[PDB]
Amino acid sequence: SHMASMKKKGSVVIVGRINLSGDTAYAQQTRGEEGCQETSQTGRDKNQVEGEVQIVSTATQTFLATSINGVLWTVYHGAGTRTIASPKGPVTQMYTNVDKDLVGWQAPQGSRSLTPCTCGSSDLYLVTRHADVIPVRRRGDSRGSLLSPRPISYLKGSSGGPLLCPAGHAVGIFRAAVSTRGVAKAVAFIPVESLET
Ligand SMILES: COc1ccc2nc(C)c(O[C@@H]3C[C@H]4C(=O)N[C@]5(C(=O)NS(=O)(=O)C6(C)CC6)C[C@H]5/C=C\CCCCC[C@H](NC(=O)OCC5(C)CC5)C(=O)N4C3)nc2c1
Ligand SMILES: [Zn+2]
Image (cartoon, rainbow, N blue to C red; front, top):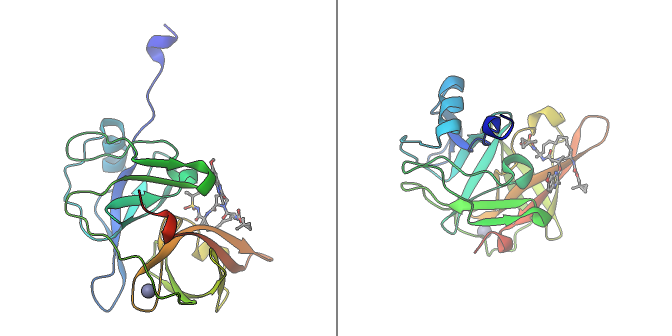
């Protein structure tokens, strides 16, 4: 039967984290490929969640998610409308705004949120899925220029990750990147002013 064969789309799965609790940033994997695919279909994730920045994956893409104001935020172009796997089953999004490329689930038990920056700083720091901390000069409300342009491959898969001020508050989450001949020159981010329900 056609309708009996209609499958359901998988959940987003936390597969790691970017640890920013010490003086080095470093990436941690908490789930391998097979475990990720299984957890995506069931939506049941019993792993203990920690930290502010999570590495997340669907069946087909991997990116980042950042907890701010008690909500785990990420980009719509990565997560779509998908639920997220949790200890008590799949969890539906708290917030969905395709016009901001922004979605949110209630933050996991055991996670912590970053503080929204109120500094009005223009010296920003983008955290990548590889735990690189990339200086960025803020341009206006939602853009920034890389101080040292790198290859665009260095940024791929880091959408949903945080841009932080010098003191470590959250200024926004990484949304898109602008390149010129394959070198990343600037980024766009969702201002933290929007990461609140
Ligand atoms: C379908 O429903 C929606 C709704 C709203 C929405 N809004 C977007 C802005 C958007 O854009 C697409 C995804 C995005 C990223 O790639 N985002 C990351 C990233 O890494 N994603 S990812 O790898 O994690 C992934 C795909 C999740 C798994 C962070 C960059 C890093 C490298 C970019 C690679 C080349 C791409 C250059 C491109 N540039 C740009 O569009 O600039 C525009 C501007 C600012 C005006 C000039 C770009 O950034 N994107 C393409 N799709 C949508 C889709
Ligand atoms: Zn600040």
